């Protein structure tokens, strides 16, 4: 699934991300847009043989096991393929773990392209 902005924002709100560890919902919607362009199926390969998976492009080196990367730690305790589902639950729950671990610094595209902007604009004009 390729979500639309307010659709994802509502789905993220209900899985408890508005304001998780001080990050408002627009931050997560913004990160999802630049990480994955809302695509629950996105996968990106990395120079170290790791892969980022799902709407939030969570990396197999630390977070999930895809059986095709070293050397990984599987700290969310899930297979990475679980992060490519149309229901964002596993990704949101893994993302809570990652920000419990330097805040949203883990997401390069977030610090690059969201941090510093009026991130609340991302959710404006949505019934939440
Ligand atoms: Pt799909
Ligand atoms: Pt849901
Ligand atoms: Pt949830
Ligand atoms: Pt603005
Ligand atoms: Pt809307």
Image (cartoon, rainbow, N blue to C red):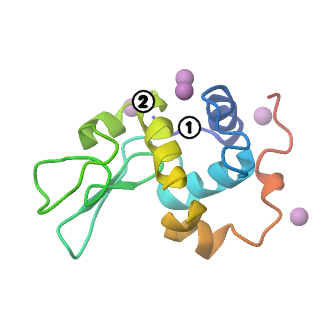
Percent across and percent down for residue 46 are 26, 70
Q: Is mark 2 within 8 Å of ligand 1?
A: yes
Residue at 61 percent across and 72 percent down: it is 111
Dividing the picture into quadrants, the one containing residue 127 is top right
Helix, strand or loop at label 1? It is loop
Residue at 54 percent across and 53 percent down: it is 99
Residue at 10 percent across and 55 percent down: it is 68
Residue at 37 percent across and 50 percent down: it is 42
Q: Measured along the vertical axis of the image, is residue 28 above or below residue 89?
A: below
Percent across and percent down for residue 54 are 39, 46
Q: Measured along the vertical axis of the image, is residue 83 above or below residue 107?
A: above
Name the quarter where the N terminus is drawn.
top left
Name the quarter where the C terminus is drawn.
top right
> Residues at badges 1 and 2 in contact (C-beta under 8 Å)?
no
Q: Left or right? Give the position of 123 relative to 30.
A: right
Percent across and percent down for residue 87 are 45, 27
Helix, strand or loop at label 2? It is loop
Q: Which mark is residue 16?
A: none
Q: Is mark 1 within 8 Å of ligand 1?
A: no
Label 1: how many Cα within 10 Å (few below 14, some 14–19, many 20+):
some
Q: Left or right? Give the position of 119 relative to 66.
A: right
Residue 14 visible in the displayed image? yes
Q: Left or right? Give the position of 16 relative to 74.
A: right
Ligand 4 - quadrant of the structure image: bottom right
Q: Left or right? Give the position of 79 relative to 70.
A: right
List the residue tagged with mark 1. 3
List the residue tagged with mark 2. 86
**Badge 1 or badge 2: first in the primary sequence:** 1
């Amino acid at each position: 699934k390729v979500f639309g902005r307010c659709e994802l924002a509502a789905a993220m709100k209900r899985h408890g991300l508005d304001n998780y560890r001080g990050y408002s919902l627009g931050n997560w919607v913004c990160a999802a847009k630049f990480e994955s362009n809302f695509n629950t199926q996105a996968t990106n390969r990395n120079t170290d043989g790791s892969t980022d998976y799902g709407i939030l492009q969570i990396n197999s080196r630390w977070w999930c096991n895809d059986g095709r990367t070293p050397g990984s730690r599987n700290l969310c305790n899930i297979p990475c393929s679980a992060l490519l589902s149309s229901d964002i639950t596993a990704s949101v729950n893994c993302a809570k773990k990652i920000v419990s671990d330097n805040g949203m610094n883990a997401w390069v595209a977030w610090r690059n392209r969201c941090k510093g902007t009026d991130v609340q604009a991302w959710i404006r004009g949505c019934r939440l």
